[PDB]
Amino acid sequence: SVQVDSVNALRKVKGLFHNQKATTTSYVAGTGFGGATYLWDANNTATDDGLSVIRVTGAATGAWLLQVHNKVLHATQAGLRAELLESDLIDQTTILQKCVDYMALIGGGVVQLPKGHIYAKAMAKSNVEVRGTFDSFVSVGSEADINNLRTVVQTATYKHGTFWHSSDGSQVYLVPENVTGAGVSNLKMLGSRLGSTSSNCGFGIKIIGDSFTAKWVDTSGFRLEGLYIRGKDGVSCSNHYFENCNFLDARRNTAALVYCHDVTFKNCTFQQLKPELTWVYLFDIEPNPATTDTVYNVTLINCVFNALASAGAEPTVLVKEQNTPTGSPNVKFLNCRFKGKATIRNNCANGWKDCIVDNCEFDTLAFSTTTTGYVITSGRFTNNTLWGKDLKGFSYNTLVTGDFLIEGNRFQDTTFENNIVATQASFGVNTFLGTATVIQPVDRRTITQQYRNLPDISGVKSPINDAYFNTEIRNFNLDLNFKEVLTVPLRSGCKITITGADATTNAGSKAYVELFVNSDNSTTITAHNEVINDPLYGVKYSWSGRTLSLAGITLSANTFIVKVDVFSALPQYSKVTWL
Amino acid sequence: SVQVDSVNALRKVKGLFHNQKATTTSYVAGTGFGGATYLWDANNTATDDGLSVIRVTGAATGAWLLQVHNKVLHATQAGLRAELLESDLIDQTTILQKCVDYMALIGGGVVQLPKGHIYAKAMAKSNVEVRGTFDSFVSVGSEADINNLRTVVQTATYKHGTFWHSSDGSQVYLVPENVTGAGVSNLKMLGSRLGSTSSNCGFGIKIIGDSFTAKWVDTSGFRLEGLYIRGKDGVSCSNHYFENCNFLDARRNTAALVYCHDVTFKNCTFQQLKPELTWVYLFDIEPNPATTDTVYNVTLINCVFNALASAGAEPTVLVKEQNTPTGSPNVKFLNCRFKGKATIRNNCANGWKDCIVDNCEFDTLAFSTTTTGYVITSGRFTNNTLWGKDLKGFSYNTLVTGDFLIEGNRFQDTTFENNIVATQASFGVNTFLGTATVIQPVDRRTITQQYRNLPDISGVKSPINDAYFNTEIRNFNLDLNFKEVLTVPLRSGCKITITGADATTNAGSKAYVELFVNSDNSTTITAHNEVINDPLYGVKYSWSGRTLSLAGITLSANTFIVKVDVFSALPQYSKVTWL
Amino acid sequence: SVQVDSVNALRKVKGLFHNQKATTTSYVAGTGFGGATYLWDANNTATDDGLSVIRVTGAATGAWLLQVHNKVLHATQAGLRAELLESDLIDQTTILQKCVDYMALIGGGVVQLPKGHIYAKAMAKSNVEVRGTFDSFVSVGSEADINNLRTVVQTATYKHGTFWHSSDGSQVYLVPENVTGAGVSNLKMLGSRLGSTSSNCGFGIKIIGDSFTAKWVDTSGFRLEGLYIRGKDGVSCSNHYFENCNFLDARRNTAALVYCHDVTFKNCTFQQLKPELTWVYLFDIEPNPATTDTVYNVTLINCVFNALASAGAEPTVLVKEQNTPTGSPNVKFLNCRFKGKATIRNNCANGWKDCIVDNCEFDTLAFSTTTTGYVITSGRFTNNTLWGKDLKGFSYNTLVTGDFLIEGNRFQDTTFENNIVATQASFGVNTFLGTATVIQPVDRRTITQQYRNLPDISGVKSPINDAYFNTEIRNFNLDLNFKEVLTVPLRSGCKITITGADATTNAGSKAYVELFVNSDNSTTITAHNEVINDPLYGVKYSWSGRTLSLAGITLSANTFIVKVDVFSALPQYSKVTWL
Ligand SMILES: [Zn+2]
Ligand SMILES: [Zn+2]
Ligand SMILES: [Zn+2]
Ligand SMILES: [Zn+2]
Ligand SMILES: [Zn+2]
Ligand SMILES: [Zn+2]
Ligand SMILES: [Zn+2]
Ligand SMILES: [Zn+2]
Ligand SMILES: [Zn+2]
Ligand SMILES: [Zn+2]
Ligand SMILES: [Zn+2]
Ligand SMILES: [Zn+2]
Ligand SMILES: [Zn+2]
Ligand SMILES: [Zn+2]
Ligand SMILES: [Zn+2]
Ligand SMILES: [Zn+2]
Ligand SMILES: [Zn+2]
Ligand SMILES: [Zn+2]
Ligand SMILES: [Zn+2]
Ligand SMILES: [Zn+2]
Ligand SMILES: [Zn+2]
Ligand SMILES: [Zn+2]
Ligand SMILES: [Zn+2]
Ligand SMILES: [Zn+2]
Ligand SMILES: [Zn+2]
Ligand SMILES: [Zn+2]
Ligand SMILES: [Zn+2]
Ligand SMILES: [Zn+2]
Ligand SMILES: [Zn+2]
Ligand SMILES: [Zn+2]
Ligand SMILES: [Zn+2]
Ligand SMILES: [Zn+2]
Ligand SMILES: [Zn+2]
Ligand SMILES: [Zn+2]
Ligand SMILES: [Zn+2]
Ligand SMILES: [Zn+2]
Ligand SMILES: [Zn+2]
Ligand SMILES: [Zn+2]
Ligand SMILES: [Zn+2]
Ligand SMILES: [Zn+2]
């Protein structure tokens, strides 16, 4: 068994036999980082890559071949310098890319990064995850105090040990199209980068590929976004999952979804807490105009959106539906907290269909619609609390329809004064606290609109179903000829009311005439009561059996309303026949 | 430390001291795979198993004991042959089963398979995962082109390196009852098998046990199903999870659920795209008739169902409720895509309760009910798109009730002509495009049916709740003697309308009589208005205080309807007492 | 390369060169457990800790430094004693805490426990998981019998090999505040503890920190709870996940949530099946009264709650909302099974808002409210089955509102007799089986209450929308001076009914007066019909154009009801102006 102190020492030692074992103490002698296990290949003439092939310098052929165990490659085993400070401005892009590429060659797995600042941009490859190292965690306080005191005793919190920068202004971690199952975890990404002291790196994570996963990742200081997801036509950009991530200050948005679907954030935060670093929005779902960009099926569970006021900044969480397959962005805010200035912005030009906000908290306005005229077409705003710590309104410049349901919410000091949403939305039970404007429950949903219009038939019946009263009403344009208008049923008593409703000035119809009928199974008696019947502008009526005919007297007096009340013992005899 | 080239060489070497380390270069000399680490046990008398115990041949005592690291056993470390072609018809079942059995013996973990074609059927054991090896991934294109071009530049996609076949026609991976927490990942399973060139292996994964997990697995070419789940009575078959799996062509169904509950598919596909290989259905939830089989609580999230036409094949995704505890299969299609000929089939003999289809896309009919008479009893068909690329209809041979809600959907050219579903379902707002049959919103739900019937009491009230109009109506069978019929309340004005509604021919009742009452807190005045009152067939009335009595004149004229209109300032005085 | 038999021997040997490799056969000589790899540091002056630093005794400098691979430290490599019996009363707390503390120092990972009983309490540290070792699994039965027989053939089930006890009566696993990302898996926790044979350990897992995860963990025999979650003010106690866990018998509750949010249980069970070991509740969500404790956002998916009767035990699953941010505890029971005596208890003093029980099974009462007067304010009780195996009732001592929806359930022999819930809740379609009390569907929801009250306007219209009948009603207190009361619209016929509804004795108003109006676009005709109009106690009316004025005749006769019927052709002319 061969044991040397560095890769340079390995290059001076030849293997005795095929696949002899060699073990390096470190990559660079005396650092304690980068040690690995190698197998001797006497015939190898591949190019020395400082990673998988270690060519012996004192021989014409021969190499020590890296053995990766447990599908984890430590980047230090390719020569990456560990535990560097941010002031060590060393481009290690080529080394890190070698690690990702080589793991992707041998079936995927994990590229482990050490602690330290690393300036090295990487192109993700399928089924490879880049993983950092948490800094040391040392708890504070005794078990007794932790158990007995309600105050905080264990004050130590975890800290990232890996700080991943880019070598230029583009991105740190690019996930190309058709790259699937890649990931990143357990590190912090920083916007400061090689090549410029004033202009930071554009993106932390830029996702074009599919099924990306990130856990315990923070992003801070990026020139555009910490996270940016935009696929391409014809290739999947979907099934992305983020948990325990903190997308912090960025000069445009903390994060942006531009072209993707089926994305989930769980226990992640989005925070613009550096007001001196001016920015644009907080969290932005914004497909680019006049492109095939589309975003839909996004779920944010137990996330925090938090913003402090900043010069020129709009503290909004934007949802922009564009060219989605169903017409809904299917974006759900569940168990989320909007803190500081954070608020939801409807950016849907063709209306926001099925907007979902449930069990969320709002420090200020729940909705702030910048574009006048945008509408939330439908949705459910349930079990939320508007704390009213800042602004006291429900929304700014927002429009909804009756298919937007507001139910189960806690309104602390929430005012709906002069807010048209209060006359548009459906309200169920809600709780009004402090000085909140109490809105009585009111149904404005489309599914129930037939119960709110005047119906086309009206009446009442006996609980025994042997007595019925039904009333219908028709508009009649009468001329001077008698016209059959209706036939009353048998076994019924009917009252017909005829009155004018004419739009003519002076010469319109004037009449209020009651006609009465009672019939058994074959025989009919009628009677009349002319309360008002102008001899020039009134109405003429005539019975032929059970068929009523009407006529006007003067053509200008032509518009009459005819209402029928039918009393019967069975529904079959409850309605007239209109002719 | 000893280092030999194979296990056979290890059998010829004794350890110098207790627990001396030995390293095999390969399992079989010169193959380059399966090498492992062993520890010397001078006292060991166990049987050589070619895996964990390597006995020195020719001695009563002495063995080299395998050292498994990180709960991962490479199957090659039991002699399994790697890198084989599909034409290498080599049964390795015994070797693979030894690895699974041994890992289950020492606490579970992973059995790692190499790249290549492997003919070896395995019985899963608890807490053991079988994992293959991805083939090498090498991306295409420069970072600049990937970032700058909207066209696809990175064209390389991941490929499986492990192709797992069976050694006979049964199944590749059997998960017995009471085997819990097993899994499979990162491989492709193929239906071609040893012993027959014409009859393929029945199943890829056959699951009888509990809490199974599969990720990044494809199934293709199986004689029955790529995936088949059927538990047994008294043992759990539940909590199964599948992600990033592709269940491809099979001669019966791509996958089938027969007896199990709480199963989730996320970002999986079900595809019958080999029409020349005839098949039965696309995806089948089908408990066997006349058994205890039952399937319920199934969620398909962001899945693709895709089928091309094939002779005798039905391109359906079938849901069959049978013996479920709640009467609902609780099957949800969320964010799914039905492509080609794919369509949902209701196969519930006792009705499909709470059918859920949300944010799904349909290339053709959404529903195709093969069995005439089957009903979708209730559910929500929300936020879906019917593209109408193939057939333009909503459904075939399908029946629903008013508790099936159709809302928020996008209907491109969808025709409901002659489709009874349009007269059965509840419709909310929907979007109708092209030549789609515009269905007005209409509520047919059971919960609201009381708003669509005629009420037993009717009227109107003031917004101040100090003025009421209430009307009730009754049928009376009168004889020649007076009978008490009602008592009007105090503090009210009342109008009683009495009219005939008799089924007798010629000799029935004829009357239209209006009675009026006004009372303060104690005093009552009455008045009458006989509009129609036949001297033989009319009605007689008499007041005793506030109690009205009625009588007929001739027995054949006996059926009268009595309607009361009550005007009052308080609800307590708003209704008569019917006697 | 040095290889010695124990750590003790390592302390007696100095390394020859920098970073020489040393390998111990065991930690303690001859045990077969705890061997590890060390690197020589000649300069080291750190303190010997029996784990990471092994100082050579008798020298001022020099130490062997532990090499941890793969982020897994085996506790045996710190001297932990493996495979001990429960009767081996050996405290290993100091060793286990060292392992957790050291892994948290070098970036987190896993502390692997061996098989056996271990008495050792541990304080969790961030991003560190404690993992046990399953006992051996050996399946039973042939593949043929497993595949061909519908009866259970594979009878072997997984067994824990690690049994984790406490060293005293407090807790086994404490997760302090600000400790994040810790976990436990693959072991069993037992309440028996060192120092007392009669008083067991209080808690198995006590969680104060954030983002805890447990999988395949059982807890049994604890004096208080197997699982207990209570955070502190100002620090997150959230995002906790449990899967495949069994919280068994405990002397108070199997598990309790006291101060936490966003907790998920999937495929877990909660079972009090040892009635001889008396207990308090089954599963308890209970913030302490008069504290800042609060619990919300809890999901239980496919869990089992199972209780046998025990003297003094209440077999309840309690939900207590207290000071939650939205007023709803947001607790969901999905796909769950309540077995034996298990039943849900509403323990919300302020009402249980948005109670969710869906696709659950109940062996007995679904709800048992111990505190008389507690209400379920709203919720959805959908797709559940009440088997009626024990008690036949739906609930005990429970109160709901109409915003509690009961729909899609299967009521087997469920009796609602004398249960006020049947008169309070909203009922949709439900299935009534056996001797069950059939409850008709009835809507009692607040959102639709405007369809059940008398409306403030009533009438009927034509399907062509060119004929309308609208009626309104008002209360008038008239004096002796004429008072303008209304103005009838143009282009309409109106019938005004005026009648008394006076509460005065003897001297109240008496009138039934009908007034009629017809107008075209400018001209108006009126008529009157005084059916009742007392000369002393009646009403006076006067028209000025379309404005009606009313006056009384005697001050004591002052209360009049005025009903207006408007007939029109246009909505603009369908209503009077009330003055
Ligand atoms: Zn390996
Ligand atoms: Zn490293
Ligand atoms: Zn730093
Ligand atoms: Zn540090
Ligand atoms: Zn910096
Ligand atoms: Zn997609
Ligand atoms: Zn699409
Ligand atoms: Zn929805
Ligand atoms: Zn509701
Ligand atoms: Zn409704
Ligand atoms: Zn005409
Ligand atoms: Zn006349
Ligand atoms: Zn006219
Ligand atoms: Zn090879
Ligand atoms: Zn290990
Ligand atoms: Zn192949
Ligand atoms: Zn291998
Ligand atoms: Zn290949
Ligand atoms: Zn089950
Ligand atoms: Zn799971
Ligand atoms: Zn996933
Ligand atoms: Zn059951
Ligand atoms: Zn449902
Ligand atoms: Zn709706
Ligand atoms: Zn009689
Ligand atoms: Zn008769
Ligand atoms: Zn008279
Ligand atoms: Zn490592
Ligand atoms: Zn161990
Ligand atoms: Zn034991
Ligand atoms: Zn054992
Ligand atoms: Zn929190
Ligand atoms: Zn989680
Ligand atoms: Zn808050
Ligand atoms: Zn809800
Ligand atoms: Zn419903
Ligand atoms: Zn019975
Ligand atoms: Zn006055
Ligand atoms: Zn008069
Ligand atoms: Zn009075």
Image: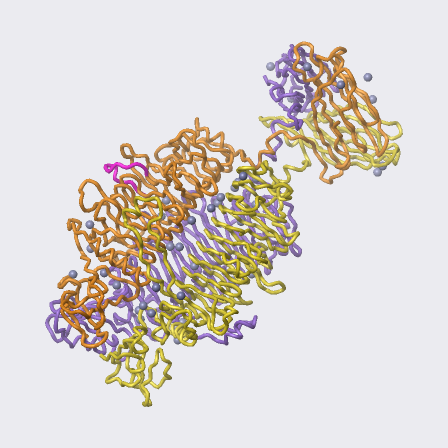
Chain colours: A purple, B orange, C yellow
Which residues, given as a range, are shown in magenta? B270-281
Q: Position of residue A294 (x, y in %)?
A: 40, 48
Q: Quadrant of residue A161?
A: bottom left
Which image quadrant is residue A328 in? top left
For this rendering, which residue is in front, B203 or A368? Answer: B203
Q: Residue C58, how many percent across, how many down? A: 32, 90
In the displayed structure, C163 sits above or below B232; it is: below
Q: Position of residue A25 (x, y in %)?
A: 25, 77
Q: Quadrant of the N terminus of chain C?
A: bottom left
When the figure is inspected, residue A242 is found, relative to residue B328, above or below; the finding is: below
Q: Is residue A339 left or right of residue B455?
A: left
Let me know if residue B327 appears in the view. yes
Where, quadrant-wise, is the C terminus of chain C in this rendering?
top right
Left or right of residue A162: residue B186: left
C45, C161: nearer the viewer? C161
Q: Which quarter of the figure has residue C96?
A: bottom left
**Can you see residue B148?**
no
> Where's residue C161, x and y in %?
37, 64
Is A237 on the left or on the right of C229, as rendered? left
Vertical placement of residue C107 versus A317, above or below: below
Q: Is residue B274 magenta?
A: yes
Closer-to-camera residue (A493/C116)? C116
Task: Give the main secondary structure, helix, strand or loop, of the magenta stretch.
Answer: loop
Tell me how many marks there are: 0
